[PDB]
Image: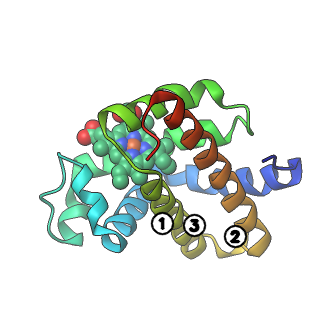
Amino acid sequence: MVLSEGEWQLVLHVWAKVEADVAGHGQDILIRLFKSHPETLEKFDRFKHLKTEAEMKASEDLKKLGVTVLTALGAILKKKGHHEAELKPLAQSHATKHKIPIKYLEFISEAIIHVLHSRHPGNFGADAQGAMNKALELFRKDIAAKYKELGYQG
Ligand code: HEM
């Protein structure tokens, strides 16, 4: 697929608002993900012992991971489709070391969209949401293809 520039502009415009508080957004998104799809929490050895959302909010480690995840995603979206290099190490670690199925990347894509929708309604109307969804579907499509070359496809 290929986004138009206009679509990239809608995606990077709301992203610039996310970047005003990267740790807060990273917490909100990971907690929305673990509440909605608790099985995903099992992939995190360091955190699968967290029992409630209060514990998750209080975890310093969880907040640090959130910033790591959002910072890598932001770097990929800022490429505007030219993200082959950025994707290579990401695909390798998520396919061989962590073993994250494509289905789980769809789940965090749903959590990202839910959080931007609640925190940025003015910059995340239907056209902006459609553009962010296209950008995350492109991201998932390119990572799924890399998973296949690497021998995981899952
Ligand atoms: C928007 C998509 C995501 C991005 C951009 C991303 C980014 C990252 C990055 C940059 C790291 C640190 C270096 C590395 O190991 O690659 C990481 C680690 C990790 N990620 Fe992902 N990730 C994403 C989705 C997920 C999902 C959906 C899961 C599981 C449901 C996941 C599981 C993990 C695990 C288990 C680690 C190691 C955490 C720790 O160090 O204990 N990631 N991820």
Which residue: 70% across, 34% down? Answer: 79
The picture quadrant where one finds residue 128 is: bottom right
Q: Is mark 3 within 8 Å of ligand 1?
A: no
Secondary-structure class at tag 1: helix
Disc 3 residue type (three-letter): Ile
Q: CA distance from mark 1 to mark 3?
A: 5 Å
Q: Give yes or no for contact between labels 3 and 2 (Cβ–Cβ under 8 Å).
A: no
Q: How many marks?
A: 3
Residue 124 image label:
2
Q: Is residue 124 above or below residue 103?
A: below
Q: Nearer the viewer, mark 2 or mark 1?
A: 1
Residue 113 image label:
3
Which residue: 75% across, 60% down? Answer: 131
The image shows residue 121 at horizontal and vertical percentages of 65, 75
- State the residue in front, 123 or 137: 137
Specify few, some or many for label 1: CA neighbours under 10 Å numbering under 14, 14-19, or 20 or more: many
- Ligand 1 location (quadrant): top left
The image shows residue 16 at horizontal and vertical percentages of 66, 51
- State the residue in front, 150 or 134: 150
Disc 2 residue type (three-letter): Phe
In the displayed structure, does residue 14 sit left or right of residue 68? right
Q: Of callouts 3 and 2, which one flags the residue occurring earlier in the amino acid sequence?
A: 3
Query: Can residue 137 be seen from the camera position used here?
Result: yes
The residue identified by callout 1 is: 111
